[PDB]
Length: 255
Ligand SMILES: Cc1ccc(C(=O)Nc2cccc(C(F)(F)F)c2)cc1C(=O)Nc1cnc(Nc2ccc(N3CCN(C)CC3)cc2)nc1
Image (cartoon, rainbow, N blue to C red; front, side, top):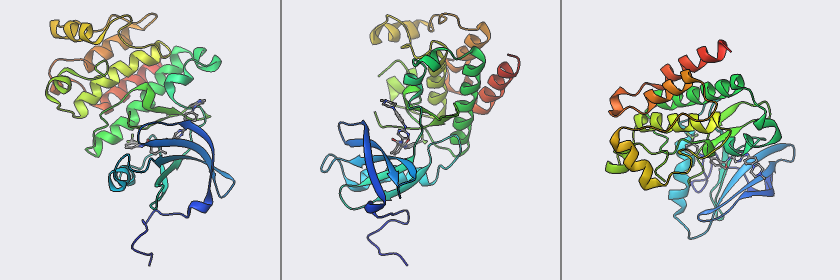
């Protein structure tokens, strides 16, 4: 029988030690730290007054119903200001930064296809739970020390957003699929920004004409055609993540 002013997932702040700022800003910060000394953790702290504690904590509640090996795992929370949200710590950071390290740069197309499927796997779970990511991109993907991936969302722009979402604010798992198509270009180009040298309005005009992003450099034609499916006009025509994972796995087992 815990006290009413504490969450079921509460832990005393004293069990945590914040060691390194991973990122800061708007509604608070993110720190790499330790739980009870031996366990590495990630900690999101709320900037007092930046937003409502309940609003902040709603994210964790959402993560409580979304536990899976391919998604960042919620560890606990501290519900007395400053409010914290604690999750597992992924050693290699964000996929976008990792792909540019001496290691990442050297990853083969086989390894990249692997990771792509992995992400597709996490999205399939998200899909089965009737959830909607809304911001699926390499910046929201975490890499572990064993080079495995996990979907995340750091609460942070056209280039990844599908037309109906941009134009009607209608986000669904289908718009996530479109965003995945784009994420796929980030993977194969080792982190390069999609639509090289194009502004947002340019991208917008191109998409309206029916043009899609130019084949990224060194991109397997088979991979490009899969991306094409993610970018179909009608949301209902884009594939499911299980299908995507299914194909990627085949490309991966053929390399
Ligand atoms: C505290 C927190 C709290 C929540 C989350 C998170 O997803 N939330 C989420 C919310 C809704 C839905 C979902 C989803 F997508 F799962 F469905 C996720 C993430 C964190 C959260 O922030 N977790 C986190 C941060 N960094 C790392 N590792 C990590 C990250 C970056 C870097 N680097 C490399 C070195 N550079 C010097 C700087 C950055 C090094 C390690 N590992 C884990």
